[PDB]
Amino acid sequence: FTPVVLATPIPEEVQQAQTEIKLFNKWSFEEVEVKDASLVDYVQVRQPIFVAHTAGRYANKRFRKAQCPIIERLTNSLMMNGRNNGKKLKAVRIIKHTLDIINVLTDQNPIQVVVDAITNTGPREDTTRVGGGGAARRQAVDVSPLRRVNQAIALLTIGAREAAFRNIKTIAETLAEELINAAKGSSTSYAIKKKDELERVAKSNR
Amino acid sequence: VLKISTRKTPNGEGSKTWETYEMRIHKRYIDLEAPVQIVKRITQITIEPGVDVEVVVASN
Amino acid sequence: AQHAVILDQEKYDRILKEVPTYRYVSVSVLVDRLKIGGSLARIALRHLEKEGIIKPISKHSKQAIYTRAT
Amino acid sequence: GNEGAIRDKTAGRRNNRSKDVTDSATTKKSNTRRATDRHSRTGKTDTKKKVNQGW
Amino acid sequence: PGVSVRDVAAQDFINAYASFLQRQGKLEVPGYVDIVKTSSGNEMPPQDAEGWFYKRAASVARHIYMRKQVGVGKLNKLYGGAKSRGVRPYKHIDASGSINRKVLQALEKIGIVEISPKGGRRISENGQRDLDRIAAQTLEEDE
Amino acid sequence: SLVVQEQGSFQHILRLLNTNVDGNIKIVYALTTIKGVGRRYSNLVCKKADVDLHKRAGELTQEELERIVQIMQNPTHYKIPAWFLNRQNDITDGKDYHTLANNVESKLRDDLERLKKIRAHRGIRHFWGLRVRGQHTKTTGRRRA
Amino acid sequence: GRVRTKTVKRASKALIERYYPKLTLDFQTNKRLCDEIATIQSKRLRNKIAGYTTHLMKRIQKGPVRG
Amino acid sequence: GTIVLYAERVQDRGLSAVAQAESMKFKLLNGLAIRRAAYGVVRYVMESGAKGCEVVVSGKLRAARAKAMKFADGFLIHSG
Amino acid sequence: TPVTLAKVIKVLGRTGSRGGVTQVRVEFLEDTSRTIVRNVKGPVRENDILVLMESEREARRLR
Amino acid sequence: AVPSVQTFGKKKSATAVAHVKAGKGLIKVNGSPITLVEPEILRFKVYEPLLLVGLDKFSNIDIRVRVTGGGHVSQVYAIRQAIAKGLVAYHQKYVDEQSKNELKKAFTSYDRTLLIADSRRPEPKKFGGKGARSRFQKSYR
RNA sequence: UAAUUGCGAUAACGAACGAGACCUUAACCUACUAAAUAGUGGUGCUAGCAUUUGCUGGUUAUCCACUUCUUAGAGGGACUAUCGGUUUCAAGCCGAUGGAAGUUUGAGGCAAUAACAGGUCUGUGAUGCCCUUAGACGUUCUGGGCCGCACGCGCGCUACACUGACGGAGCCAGCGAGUCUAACCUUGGCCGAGAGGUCUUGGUAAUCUUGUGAAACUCCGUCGUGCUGGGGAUAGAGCAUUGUAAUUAUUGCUCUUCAACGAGGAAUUCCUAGUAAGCGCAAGUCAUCAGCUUGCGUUGAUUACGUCCCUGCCCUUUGUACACACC
Ligand SMILES: [Mg+2]
Ligand SMILES: [Mg+2]
Ligand SMILES: [Mg+2]
Ligand SMILES: [Mg+2]
Ligand SMILES: [Mg+2]
Ligand SMILES: [Mg+2]
Ligand SMILES: [Mg+2]
Ligand SMILES: [Mg+2]
Ligand SMILES: [Mg+2]
Ligand SMILES: [Mg+2]
Ligand SMILES: [Mg+2]
Ligand SMILES: [Mg+2]
Ligand SMILES: [Mg+2]
Ligand SMILES: [Mg+2]
Ligand SMILES: [Mg+2]
Ligand SMILES: [Mg+2]
Ligand SMILES: [Mg+2]
Ligand SMILES: [Mg+2]
Ligand SMILES: [Mg+2]
Ligand SMILES: [Mg+2]
């Protein structure tokens, strides 16, 4: 890659994959495509990032929250349940770890796996408590792609976090695990269940 | 800036409204080399109600 | 209390022959295979590295990770 | 004195705990009057001359 | 090329310096080690048991190298941590002036630090010497 | 550290100080189930006894165990400070003690009684089942007895 | 809501009324105009004014504006 | 000797609030109709060429229950 | 399973007494030239793509 | 006097001052090399400028930074801003315009506000809550 | 529209108070004036490592220069600008580009007319009237009490752990405050495990404490799901500090003792971006005592960018036998 050095030196694999490709912790942003139409737009990938940390003014306008890199939207949503409010660095590291884990199992761009599990847990339709007079039925609705992404990111991490609670297996594993079983849905995952059982009730009342 | 932060109320009733007065202290210093005459001249005059003037001496 | 705090010779031998096919090994993973608690499990992660089987691809505290040797 | 205190039965925790709690405990605000706020009790009244002299 | 200690990351250095003061034998280690606690804002003594006085000294050394002059009071405030007052909100608390002031004398009597003017202690000329040395040793394992 | 081995040499659970102790636990903490030996005390004692803390209660030679008990019930001899002790400056013979095991129960009694028997308000208050260290007794502590 | 108060619109009206030649589709010179040509006590109010006598001017050039 | 006092009349009392409060006090303390008192104060302040002026009188006057009047004229602003 | 893709072609308003729901007209991409109005759950702008899980059935008012 | 410039970077309260003189390509912060910095997870955040715009670029210059204020992260974003702002300052007075304006382009496109300082800042708290927006608790009755 | 904020309709035209303007603070100036009580580069004097120039430090003045950073004066800056969608092509609203900044730029200060038997006579040597006035309801001195404990309610703190506790190690803020006729803020040196003690010292302060080396946090180890090394109530014994006085335990330290609590029913609070939440700090109080408050900065999200369903309130319309106004 035509190596270059000056005074205080810059590491080999650092010099290397940096100036060449523009990739993640050390993972490919090329390839990596959203196998479900829609959800593109509402899932970033390219522009590429180094790590998922970004002072990104993503909230001052309604939809621009979509432009946040999906990987980092996935981390961002780890840093919650009070005790872990803030603590991005905490999350970021988990994610690094997670993707390493995911990659170990079944190869694949772990960042592409993350794509699949998200794509694969967004409820195509749901329900809402319409009135109809005191005794409320449940009107079926086709839900937004954005909500579908959001709800996916929430659903994913949560059921991981919950499983991760009170046992030896670490967050980063259960997170990976939840994603792995969700990249191609297996109904052994927290999210796929809730996804499917949200569309269950949705169907059941139309 | 000298803050003083107080409840408005003489007593205790009412939503707890708090209110902070403040006083701004501005201080300059101007270094001069002059003989005895101009000093005393320039110091007695230039007086001003509200400006506190302090003239010292020495290098220690 | 519920077992995995020692080494029972058969356990050691168990640990050598039972770690292929493990695409994943870590602290958790070792306790999971109905054996070794997080402490002596951690020791295994250094002494399986003594030579062979495990490749160190991830760094540190809490999270460990290896794969079968090549 | 203190000797009295320790010796005296009918005292200490064990005893109170075995007693039934009065209902005046779990009461209310009591309130008493407020609906009468705007109705002056003095029974007196001013008078349109005296206010006109003053004001 | 030339070398400082600023050219080496924290941990690799201080452990390399811990290993060195240990390997040495020359030190002066009070005696109440292992029986002492390093701060009132702590719960258990250090887990290095045999050692950690090196860990600190090495930590001490590097810090006083990094700057003009520091005292015992500064190291206390530096080295201290959070003390859970059990059920009552945490507050910062200073660490032990003994552990440090003895480490300061231990590194001084070994000539790695001297009682600076202005105040406190300043990195000895011979401290520089031996610090920048093992610093260079630390990058030589990386070569 | 090291993959170890051993034979049938270690037995699980092992009684000392008139109480019982689980083997398969790191010996430092194992000893704490004895009344009157917090983690700190445990820590210093084993450090004194020349025993490897990386070991469990499980291993630990019988001789090692014997030494460990020894120091515990004679702390001033085996150069343990004094401010490290649960009963400095008694209140009768003034010696410094580390009251251990089934005995700390005995001594809580002795003192408590001493107070009551002396009619001291502290005692009176102890006898009444209330809190003594001068806390508000209105809202807190309701379940209790 | 950036709805301009009366005084801003009041004054813009009057300025276009009697100084149409001089003024433009340019606030930046409309500004400088207001200094020389009008007395105001604050920068913000002058800008808030000039920006609107601008806008008013910018849509006179294509159709009249009532008032 | 280190301290020195001088008196000094003030350019128009009619534009000093504090000059006019103390006026009313002295108007009413000297037994004067209430409206008359303030309405004089307002009418002198105005004539002293102010842009506007306001006199509140709160409290209790000869009747038992308290009241409060406002006497204003001309121009005042109240904010900022 | 018949999956049906439709593109939002206008935003009509919020229904639902609550108001979390929005009325929108879409155009399916697998053969256009026909339109149906659906009810969303999450936030929507123009040019979005809804997964009509059942192709033909529409709502109007919501209480 | 060799060719040199001075620049800064600010995130929150952190301010990062950088001196970019001409030399043999050093890049040290406060007193240590840029390969340290740790945070570490965020290490690449500050490597970022050099990689965005070709590692070479730095061979004819020395680079130093010294951050005060801010916090363990506020400073990481500060120092990188100063680095890239400096690289573009230097090509403004010394190299030609088009190289400079080709550098702005590579930074602005990618970006994380490398040239442009983030405006955000703590809002004052007001009385009646532990936060600014946060209000205490009430109970009615 | 946040706004009787505007457009528009128009027997009204055109105005003022209030809103806005205004003011204060946080944002932007390699433009202006400067600074040994702020800091940068060069120079000597000098240390360490490399030596081939280099790298990293010491040196309140050994000198020269500068104002990017800090400070605060004077200016400038933004007007929702340009462009485009949308709309009675109106006030506007929405998107893109630019921009320090485009949610009233963010946050406060100020705030018309009126109402309340709101609260305060316990802040006032503000005050009417009533009461009391020497066995006093004046005042002061000694001691107790406001903390008293079957229980009901509210604001909080700490937790139930493995996004963790622990032990090393990294090491980063901002708003403040400090002693004269006095004992305030305290660096540094010793002594002590600790709390602390002792010797000195700088500061009436951008000059010294103090870079307030704050805490979450980051890193390497230990523990390994077990009421466990989570949790630290209750209690024993000892040591110190404030104070004339510490018992009903002011506070601080050490040892031991090791509770409830395994995420909390009906219910219900707060909140839209550097916000929420996590986190510590300074100031008030203060001899001694913060689990309170007022501010401060550190880390930093998820979810709306809507509606009238609940609740609250405003506006019309309408009824009134009320106007002391549905108490
Ligand atoms: Mg906490
Ligand atoms: Mg620490
Ligand atoms: Mg610290
Ligand atoms: Mg015990
Ligand atoms: Mg006005
Ligand atoms: Mg206003
Ligand atoms: Mg400047
Ligand atoms: Mg932009
Ligand atoms: Mg009343
Ligand atoms: Mg009063
Ligand atoms: Mg009380
Ligand atoms: Mg309250
Ligand atoms: Mg820690
Ligand atoms: Mg002693
Ligand atoms: Mg002095
Ligand atoms: Mg426990
Ligand atoms: Mg604990
Ligand atoms: Mg205080
Ligand atoms: Mg209070
Ligand atoms: Mg009527």
Image (cartoon, rainbow, N blue to C red):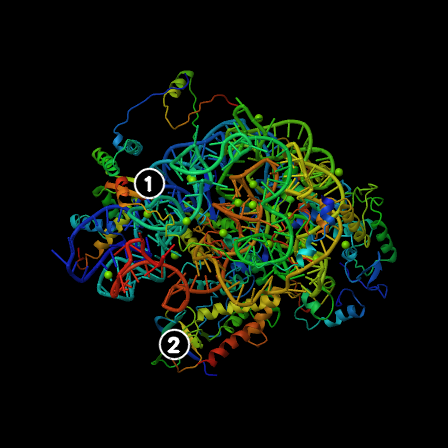
**Quadrant containing the C terminus of chain F in the rendered view:** bottom right
Query: Disc 2 designates what residue?
Result: I38
Q: Which residue is nearer to you in this view: C45 or A189? A: A189
Label 1 element class: loop
CA–CA distance in space, label 1 to label 2: 70 Å
How far from the left and from the top, in percent, is residue C65? 65, 65
Q: Quadrant of ligand 20?
A: bottom left
Amino acid carrying label 1: it is Lys
Q: Which residue is nearer to you in this view: C65 or G35? A: G35
Indicate left or right for J108 with J44 as reference: left
Furthest-right residue in view?
F63
How far from the left and from the top, in percent, is residue H1? 41, 16
Instruction: Judge whether F18 appears above or below K250 on screen.
Output: below
For mark 1, does the 10 Å Cα neighbourhood hold few (<14), some (14 to 19), or many (20 or more) residues? some
**Quadrant containing the N terminus of chain F in the rendered view:** bottom right
Q: Could you say which quadrant of the image residue K50 lies in?
A: top right
How many numbered discs sit on the rendered protein?
A: 2
Q: Are marks 1 and 2 on the same chain?
A: no
Label 2 element class: strand
Query: Disc 1 designates what residue?
Result: H60
How far from the left and from the top, in percent, is residue J16? 50, 46
Whether the residue carrying mark 2 lies under 8 Å from ligand 8 is answered with no
Q: Which residue is nearer to you in this view: C17 or F6? A: F6
Amino acid carrying label 2: it is Arg
Image point 39% across, 83% down: which residue? I56
Q: Could you say which quadrant of the image residue C18 lies in?
A: bottom right
Q: Chain of mark 1?
A: H
Q: Which residue is nearer to you in this view: K327 or E72? A: K327
User: Is residue E44 at least partly visible in the picture?
Assistant: no
Q: Chain of mark 2?
A: I
Question: Are the residues tagged 1 and 2 within 8 Å (C-beta)?
Answer: no
Q: Which label sits in the foreground, 1 or 2?
A: 1
